[PDB]
Image (cartoon, rainbow over all chains, first blue to last red; front, side):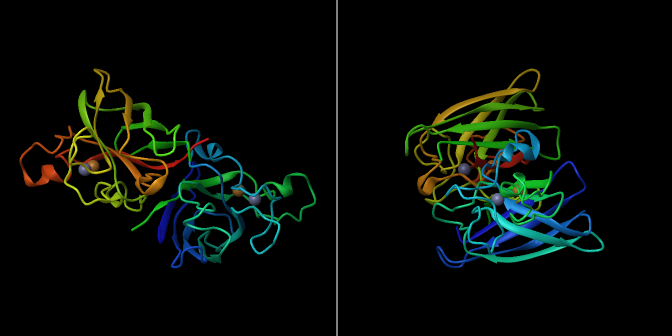
Length: 153
Length: 153
Ligand SMILES: [Cu+2]
Ligand SMILES: [Cu+2]
Ligand SMILES: [Zn+2]
Ligand SMILES: [Zn+2]
């Protein structure tokens, strides 16, 4: 798996398409695409553990966290494998996503293929909210849109 | 990955949920669940190559076929890794799926996690339709509903 893709959908008007590319095995992973229907500003953005959409986005479960760490920001050291921090929405509620990250992988046992990607109601506080919940979801809030991450051409 | 799941959706009224379980590494894989909104009778049922739903189900691409074989039935020897043959709809258009298969896998390089599952308009003819198209799609027809296959709890 060099490439992947994911279509985000939800009950909301929120929706988008996000691509992944890992040119090198165990190298970094460019993540990019575009989401629309967001409130202007920051929104949390994570890979969650399961490709389950049985019961909407709640089925996805908690943040993908195979090394059992506390939640954090993507550049933080103590973080969930799935913690990609935030994405930023336009005036117009379009967020033009573009991220490199080398904690996640499309191969290996950090492989995120088959897991749900989720964009959230509010900003991820990157674990620095000082409340119980911040070291788990980053207080990112409810799950506005999501989709399973799949192997792309 | 012991278990997986996939939610089938489409433009049609067709929809359902399908589960997967592979108790042994490289063993067989129980596939079961239920789909509704079908025309009574047989309907083709395959894993296609890609977890792409960019442009509905067409983005999924051709049948998952990593050994470059000709299309067949699931118990046939010459078959696509993704050829699970058919599923059967009620009077009421509910199909109660239940299948063992050991060509597909949730691990290894027949891993189908991250690929689209698709249920089709007509019956898969298992390659025996004698026409060009029958050794590719089994003449199964258009793509009524589909979804990416993801890692389940
Ligand atoms: Cu999250
Ligand atoms: Cu097909
Ligand atoms: Zn997290
Ligand atoms: Zn086939």
